[PDB]
Length: 49
Length: 48
Ligand SMILES: *[C@@H]1O[C@H](CO)[C@@H](O)[C@H](O)[C@H]1NC(C)=O
Image 1 (cartoon, chains in turn orange, purple):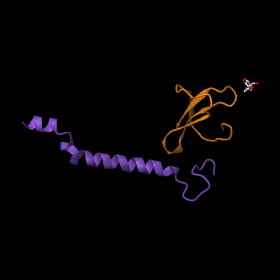
Image 2: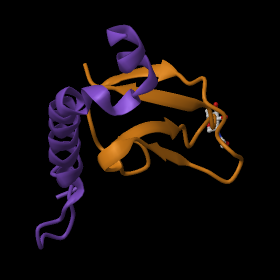
Image 3: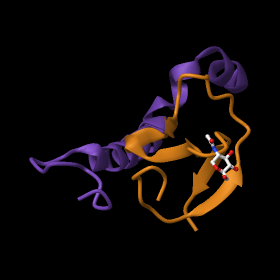
Image 4: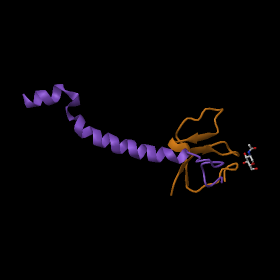
């Protein structure tokens, strides 16, 4: 439950360069592909189990 | 000359590439139709 976004999946350290003004990432069909932690601001990749 | 005819013309196998393109397009549109709200408040059952 990331700042309100609720879902399921495996969290992995991201390797894509989020710009400092971005907070979320999306694949095709509005699928949330990545998210940054609201606490440590690290980018995380979301993959369905 | 058969090989030259197949090499010079890139669109020679279009009748065979068309089915693959159609299948890919069908799958792509079926995947993209998930973002449709269909009149609902949102397109994500999690948020709903
Ligand atoms: C929030 O608090 C945790 C633990 O107190 C800390 O590790 C983290 O850096 C804090 N984040 C911010 C943005 O202050």
